[PDB]
Image (cartoon, rainbow, N blue to C red):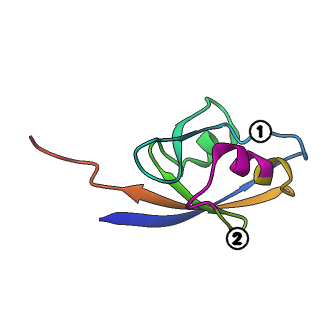
Amino acid sequence: SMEILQVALHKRDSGEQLGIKLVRRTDEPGVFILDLLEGGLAAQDGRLSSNDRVLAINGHDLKYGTPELAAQIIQASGERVNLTIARPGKPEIEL
């Protein structure tokens, strides 16, 4: 299964970073979050997580995106930044 969630953040100046690490993988399409930076915008919000997939930013489609593209969108963004995420696969397992 997977969970779709929407995160809204707010930059406090045009030039603020979100505090997010984005990567691509050679094995499946899309951009993913690798980790959040300590004390950053994304961490404080407390809603994004490692291995989340970014499906969209500001209604722009990134399901087949690159990390350059997402940066482009966020560096151009106004002060509000809405993320649409896919979170994959069971956080508790006994094995």
Is 14 in front, or is 27?
27
The answer to whether 25 appears left or right of 38 in the picture is: left
Q: Image point 36% across, 55% down: which residue? A: 88
Q: Image point 83% across, 40% down: which residue? A: 16
The answer to whether 90 appears left or right of 27 in the picture is: left
Look at the image and say whether residue 27 sits in the magenta stretch. no
Q: Specify the amino acid type for callout 2.
A: Gly
Q: Which mark is residue 62?
A: none
Instruction: Check disc 1 and report its element: helix, strand or loop.
Output: loop
The quadrant of the picture occupied by the C terminus is top left
How far across and down, in percent of the image, does residue 80 sit? 79, 60
How far across and down, in percent of the image, does residue 66 sit? 63, 48
Give the alpha-carbon distance from disc 2 to disc 1, as whole Å: 19 Å
Bounds of the magenta segment: 62-72
Residue tagged by mark 1?
A: 17
> In this picture, is 56 found above or below 53?
below
Mark closer to the chain start, 2 or 1: 1
Q: Image point 65% across, 32% down: which residue? A: 39
Rendering quarter of residue 71: top right
The answer to whether 23 appears left or right of 87 in the picture is: right
The answer to whether 92 appears left or right of 24 in the picture is: left
Is 32 in front, or is 45?
32
Instruction: Check disc 2 and report its element: helix, strand or loop.
Output: loop
Residue tagged by mark 2?
A: 59
Look at the image and say whether residue 71 sits in the magenta stretch. yes
